[PDB]
Image (cartoon, coloured by chain):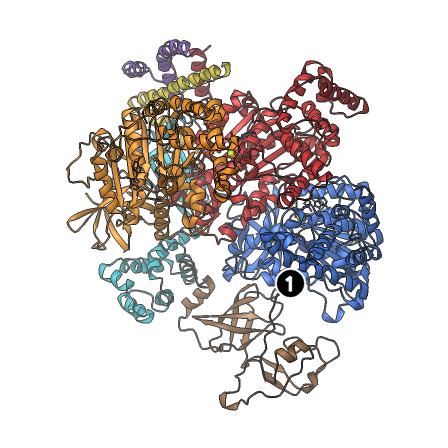
Chain colours: A yellow, B purple, C orange, D blue, E red, F brown, G cyan
Amino acid sequence: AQAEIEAERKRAREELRKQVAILAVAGAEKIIERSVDEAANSDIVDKLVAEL
Amino acid sequence: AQAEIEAERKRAREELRKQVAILAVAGAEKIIERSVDEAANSDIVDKLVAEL
Amino acid sequence: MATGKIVQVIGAVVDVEFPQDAVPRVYDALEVQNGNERLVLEVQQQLGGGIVRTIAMGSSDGLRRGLDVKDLEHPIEVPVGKATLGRIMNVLGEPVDMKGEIGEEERWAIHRAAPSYEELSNSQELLETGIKVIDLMAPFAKGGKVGLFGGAGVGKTVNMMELIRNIAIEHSGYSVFAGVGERTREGNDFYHEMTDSNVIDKVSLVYGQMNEPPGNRLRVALTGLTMAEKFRDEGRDVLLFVDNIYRYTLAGTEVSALLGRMPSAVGYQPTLAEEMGVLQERITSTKTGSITSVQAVYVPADDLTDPSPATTFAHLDATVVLSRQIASLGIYPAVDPLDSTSRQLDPLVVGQEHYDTARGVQSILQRYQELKDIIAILGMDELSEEDKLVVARARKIQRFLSQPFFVAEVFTGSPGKYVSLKDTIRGFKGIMEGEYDHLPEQAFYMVGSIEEAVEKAKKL
Amino acid sequence: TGKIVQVIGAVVDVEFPQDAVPRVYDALEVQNGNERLVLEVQQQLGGGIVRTIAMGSSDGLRRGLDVKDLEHPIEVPVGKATLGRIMNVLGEPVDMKGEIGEEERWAIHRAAPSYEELSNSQELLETGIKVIDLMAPFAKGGKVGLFGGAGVGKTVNMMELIRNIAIEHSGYSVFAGVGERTREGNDFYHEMTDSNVIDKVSLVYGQMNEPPGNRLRVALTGLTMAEKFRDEGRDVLLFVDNIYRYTLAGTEVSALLGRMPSAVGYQPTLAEEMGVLQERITSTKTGSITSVQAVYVPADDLTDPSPATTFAHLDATVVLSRQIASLGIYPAVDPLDSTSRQLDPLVVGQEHYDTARGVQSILQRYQELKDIIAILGMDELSEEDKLVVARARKIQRFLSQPFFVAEVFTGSPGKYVSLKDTIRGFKGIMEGEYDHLPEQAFYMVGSIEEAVEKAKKL
Amino acid sequence: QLNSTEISELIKQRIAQFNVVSEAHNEGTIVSVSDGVIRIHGLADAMQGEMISLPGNRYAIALNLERDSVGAVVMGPYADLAEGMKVKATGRILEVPVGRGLLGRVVNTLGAPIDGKGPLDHDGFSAVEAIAPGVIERQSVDQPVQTGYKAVDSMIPIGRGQRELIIGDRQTGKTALAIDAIINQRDSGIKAIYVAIGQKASTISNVVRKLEEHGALANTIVVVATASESAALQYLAPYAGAAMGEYFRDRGEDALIIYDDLSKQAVAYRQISLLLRRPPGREAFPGDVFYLHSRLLERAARVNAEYVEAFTKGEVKGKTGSLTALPIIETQAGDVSAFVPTNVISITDGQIFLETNLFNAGIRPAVNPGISVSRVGGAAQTKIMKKLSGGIRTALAQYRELAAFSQFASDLDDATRKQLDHGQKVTELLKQKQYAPMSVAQQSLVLFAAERGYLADVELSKIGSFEAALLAYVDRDHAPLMQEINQTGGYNDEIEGKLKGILDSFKATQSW
Amino acid sequence: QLNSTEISELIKQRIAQFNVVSEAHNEGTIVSVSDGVIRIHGLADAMQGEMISLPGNRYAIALNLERDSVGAVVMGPYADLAEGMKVKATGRILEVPVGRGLLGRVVNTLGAPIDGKGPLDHDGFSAVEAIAPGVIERQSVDQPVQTGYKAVDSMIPIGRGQRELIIGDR
Amino acid sequence: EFITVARPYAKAAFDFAVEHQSVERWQDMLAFAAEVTKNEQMAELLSGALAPETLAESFIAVAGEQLDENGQNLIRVMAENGRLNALPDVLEQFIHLRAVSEATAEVDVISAAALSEQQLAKISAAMEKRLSRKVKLNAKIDKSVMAGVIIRAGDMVIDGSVRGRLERLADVL
Ligand SMILES: Nc1ncnc2c1ncn2[C@@H]1O[C@H](COP(=O)(O)OP(=O)(O)OP(=O)(O)O)[C@@H](O)[C@H]1O
Ligand SMILES: Nc1ncnc2c1ncn2[C@@H]1O[C@H](COP(=O)(O)OP(=O)(O)OP(=O)(O)O)[C@@H](O)[C@H]1O
Ligand SMILES: Nc1ncnc2c1ncn2[C@@H]1O[C@H](COP(=O)(O)OP(=O)(O)O)[C@@H](O)[C@H]1O
Ligand SMILES: [Mg+2]
Ligand SMILES: [Mg+2]
């Protein structure tokens, strides 16, 4: 009976962990799209061509 | 034991609402080299907070 | 707007050329206007160059090269839920009865994956069918597969109607019937026997009549299964009847040969075990509800080694055999207690009282068969008192496996009986250990509970 | 100088300049990451394309790798330096000992000896085994084949023949491992080293875990060493661990070479591939190879084309059967199918010949009675048909024998039976001088004496 | 304690780990899709046996490098792929997570977990295709693997690093025997792996729940490919399982691996092979079907200490590792002479043959002697088990043959009568219940009582009672000997004398 | 879609001159070698069943005449041959030494002595493939061929000019 | 699809065209041959079962402004094997063989923002250091990248798009 309860802790812990991770990238998507319509692009591409 | 998990399930998700906002902001500034001043971003993270 | 064009028509197989960026995915559905009728195509293979190979869900006659093909971006979708009870549909979920258009609050695609590992029920419940022979000798797991290994003549359909009745009344389940490759005649008079027995409002009918092209017959099995998946998702326990699982296998062979894939084994398709697994693994008990299935099985050449039987028997849990001889005795239902089996008969799942009782009546009936050969060659004078006691109890057990159905009242005129599992265990425990030896065997025939047997006896 | 241009399974296609294309069977070489891979050329296609079988793992090949053309066949270490050592198909050392100090290397592809060079001998070779040199005696310098399905004693019999023949053989011995369990090979190597006989045995292993090109060519490497010891003028033993695997590794490759399938899906060239190996494992006027070959028969089917074409290449054939092994009778030899070229009145003498034909005649007549015995049982037989059945069952049990390699299984001590002693026993049973002993007395006894002694113990 | 902070800090670590600097990769386009086979144009830098990463988190395996295309098979649901999608080449050859942190997990054949227990901890990756240790790197097998069951430990002993086929018809106890072997290693220090190929998901979940019910689950890895999943996942399922088992072998530990149906793997490979139009052979399998099962099973090995030292760069000295394999084959109507059964019988070190006629007669586990064998032999037994078992196998085979002729006519000559009584009492003594394993001290008493004649005067209907009372008698009083025989399986004249006194006193003094 | 021995340097020769010169129709080049079958390009005058001469002293038989290919089988050790070797068609069908002096000899199928007793004393050559005597050129079989086995010469007689199958297992 | 049978003809034509220096004439010759293949009335003809020789000389008559001694010869060889529908693919492989021999490559630049000329300039220098070949950059504007630049040297891709960096982050978690 104890091992059955221990598996439920693991399953709850992972269930919540999954949700925070999708919400983080969903937030970064919305944050980035609004905030990058600038010469900030020029910053990224200059580093890329320097690395390229 | 399951009923004890139900109580913590409510408590844990409310904590991750507020922590999701911090992680999403940190991940966006990881993804683009230049950081963001949050000027129009409060309304964005608050919708993230509200869903969880 | 339509955007593909037919490039080839070779019998039932139709090839279509879409633009290079818009190529349909596998099992997508397409529509063409074949004269003044639409025809649906199901995609099977993406060849190169934007050409896609499909099979026609209907007659390919009258298709030209150069027709315009319209791309539905989903698989074949069918109506689901309560609005489909008592209706008759084809493969496509169109009404083939003339009762007109269906309600259709929702439509679902026929193609899905099975339940995932965390969705399966963490328990192993039984289904209480209400029939004494079945619930004792061949109990059903809830969400199991059962094979009906009997030929017609024996009550197959009345047994099917009795299960439909008991699961609708004595539980709150619905049923779906899938007529895979059925003769149109038997499809017609199965519908009338259900409508004239008031079970029709509690079952949905999808019929694939044999005169339809092979692609129709294969996909009908999936149309039934997706309707049962809806009733499961509503939280019910559901029965799915498949009118022949062999005809699903053979429809998959014919389609595979039309597509030109190399044959396997005894000329079957190479995908035989996968296509059976794709059907049978959707029929399970989940954490919301379950689908139990009862499947008619035909064994080719009487050969249990042939790949179709050998593949099917990997999936069956119980196995009910119906007998012409038991019907000749007048014993109904005509289940054979010695060849019917279930892998739910173990103490670890069914418990030791039920296991011991089922093992007991099997031993008594087997011993009786041997004694009945000795009687045939040498008469009853050879039997000892122990043998006469065994023969007597065996006749009482045989009588008491009979039952009156609410479906059979048309003939017997007796009211039907639903017998709980406890009452069957009490009855056979009693008869085996020699209680009720003092009342005659005809008191047990067609009666009901064992408490009803003695009350029959009192004036018999 | 060439580039890989296709890679299908174990088969690799390479493109070369038109003036530089390799000959057939030349060896190519490729860097496969940190490994070296050898490719053997099978076919020349049009246009400087050449198609090859990889002598190693094909995984990790890209297209466009540079291939180097070594302008000679696969060549292996040969001669007295190859003795007591374990080798790859490629002749590389596989024991942890150092380099092989070879003075000479030979190509593994060779022609068979001329018809003018062959030689014949009637000299019987005696073995410890009652049934084998009663029913299928074999001679110095001849070929022996053990046929059987899976798990019927092909290996145990060959391991007894290694023990018993090495009693009277002084010269060197070669063992080709083609497609058999590695564990066996390791057990055999430790048996040979712990008994110090290893100093006279040369071993080639290409076991069943290795990819098809190894298993095909490793048989030829084993022969090429035995052909050196023969051409030095010695007389030699060659044991081949399972010759069926050579033809099967040819089947696994054949369709990838672009050849239409033949018969039960075999390669069309099956009978030539089998002949071109078997015809060079022979004795000659300079020296002699004596060889025992195991021949697996798939699904117990003695009529499959691979077993069927192998039967023509052998002098003595011993046919094992599962039905006899299931009755406990070991060695599970079938006296009604096992035969030899050497069972002639002139070669073995009349008494041996007449005893062997007597045993076959009785055992065949017992087979003719089994259908009536099956339906009606024995009481409906004729009164001398009951006597035939009683002698045949005693003969069946007296063919069984304890083996010194089977003590790990039976636990019973092993037995060696001389030819004179076995023919006297069978002749005495057929004359009926033992017709008063029970059947169980004949089971697992070395000599007739031991049967009468065992009948005294019941 | 479930803690929200430690989840947040873990995500913060992954956000900190992420590398923004990109890498050039070689690319290709899907050209064709059918039945899980793919044809790709591009991928000039691909290698055979590579993993191609597709849209989604799915992968495909590169099978053929044609002149102007790659042929590949999709490892998952293939149906949402389309012509023109881009695919990316990972430099990895097909790899599977490996390590001891896998114990207690249910895992897909790609190594992704199927259970709810979250992301995996692994000690890197191991390659799915490997060639086994060569002939010089093996060692002889000389240590037991004790199952629960009187019948197989006495008659068909299994050594550490042996390969032992479990064969029979359906519904004969093949799985029950294999999971009872797993459970009896629960305390013996041998790690276990169970690979389910083409099985029903309901059955797989019930097996896992029975492993957990007995506490064995913490010592097992479970690898799943259900009957619903694409044929490529089934075909590669046992190769993935082998790659995890090799981790323990190469570190000098012992592991036991069960392959739940190699006949179902062969069918899946036959499907893929025929969809690639490869010319079929006998019973329509390709000739590669021997090579398929050969290269799998020939990795179940025992390796000498010089291999373990050289592999582990000297971090482990003097130990010897092993991987023990019990493949299962289902055979039609008991036919031991069909193709795939005969292929695997020719790869393993023996077979345990389970007969439906015995099983239906209630003789369970239904082991058929005479067919069953262990080529490794007694070297797998403990001395006491080796000495006490002896000829019990061949005596049972002969008793079954004698019973066949004895059914046919009456010729009873007293010693026949006693031979029949003894054989009937031994078979009634060798049947045993599921999930009731008994230790070597218990088995050696049972074998001692059978062959020292003590079951004289004992009725057949009393045999099961006689043992249950005897094992309780020795559990109650002469317990210290049991602890001695279970520690060192040593057979002496001292121990034989103590056993003789125990059986003399029980037979004389007790009742059953 | 697959190629048909259309290959780069041959096509470029066709580019330079499509109506390529008559040259000799007598000769050609090996383009493939495998399993003892060779494909030859050219040989416009090769007849079906004709002997083709190969480098060294070896021959092949032309069995397939196809659209710009000849398939030929090699009558000996093939593995020494290579792509781009020249070959010349003879005028000859296969012929073999024949005569009375062959009695007591052992020969291969080309009639070369294999017993080592030295060269043959044949009586000219005969074609290996020939047509049988027609219906009007036969006569009925009436003389015996004596086998010497009681069972055969009694039950199953063989006459001069009969064709008697011996059939059985190994 | 004629991708595999076109190679021999593309290679043989390119070698001959190289020997006689007329590569630039051969390409216009092949482009005209590719364009006659697409005509509505001709693609019906090419599918019919006319005899090869009759088919060839009909196509050759339409193919005025081709190098009668050499360009026509190739069409004749191909038709004699009946592969003329490979000519539009032979054209592309001819262009590729030239681009290899000229040590010259074409690569594509994709971004949501139209690139400023200094960005394009530095890319061209960088790629001509990453390659031996010269590069002709092509500008494609696609809002998909959101930010950054996608470098597409045919099969070889270097990703510098934010979106790419995002959907590569989502899988780490
Ligand atoms: N003479 C014998 N006495 C007792 N048992 C034997 C004897 N011969 C064989 N056996 C039993 O049968 C087994 C099978 O024979 P063997 O070990 O030679 O395998 P095999 O028949 O060669 O099969 P494979 O071809 O796969 O090696 C032996 O290992 C042993 O278990
Ligand atoms: N020792 C035993 N005694 C009695 N019954 C047993 C025993 N072991 C197994 N069984 C019964 O055998 C039946 C089948 O068990 P199991 O599924 O393991 O056999 P199987 O042959 O592996 O089946 P399958 O072939 O479906 O995988 C079950 O009813 C099980 O309870
Ligand atoms: N419980 C029952 N009572 C009376 N008759 C029955 C009963 N069960 C079956 N029968 C009879 O069995 C016969 C065949 O039944 P049916 O369902 O038509 O079988 P099938 O449809 O397979 O031919 C019919 O005469 C039916 O009345
Ligand atoms: Mg063997
Ligand atoms: Mg099982």
| Left or right: D221 as drawn, with respect to F41 | right
Crowding near pointer 1: few (<14 within 10 Å), some, many (20+)? some
Quadrant of the rendered structure where residue C320 is? top left
So how many labels did they put on this image? 1
Quadrant of the image occupied by residue E440:
top right
Determine whether the beta carbon of the residue marked 1 sits less than 8 angstroms from the nearest atom of ligand 4: no
Choose between F92 and D357: the one closer to the eye: D357
* Residue C20 seen anywhere in this rendered image of the structure: no
Is residue G60 visible from the viewing direction of this image?
Answer: yes
Q: Name the residue located 45 percent from the left edge and 77 percent from the top edge.
A: F22
In the image, residue E30 lies at what x, y percent?
A: 38, 43
Coordinates of residue F100 in the picture (x, y in percent): 68, 87
Give how far across and how far down residue D356 sits, in percent: 75, 61
The one nearer the camera, D173 or E453, is E453
In the image, farthest residue toward the front: C381
Q: Is mark 1 on a helix, strand or loop?
A: helix
> In which quarter of the view is residue D140 placed?
bottom right
Residue E163 as seen in the image, left or right of residue D436: left
In this view, the residue in front, E364 or A51, is E364
Residue type at the position of mark 1: Gly
Residue positioned 25% across, 43% down in the render: C187
Question: Which chain letter goes with mark 1?
Answer: D
Asked whether, in this view, residue D381 is left or right of residue C202, the answer is right
Q: In which quarter of the image is the C terminus of chain E?
A: top right
Which residue corresponds to mark 1? D275
Figure check: C55 above or below D276: above
Seen from the viewer's position, the closer of residues C265 and C400 is: C400
Residue D387 placement (x, y as % from top left) = 72, 56
In the rendered view, does E323 fall on the left or right side of D414?
left
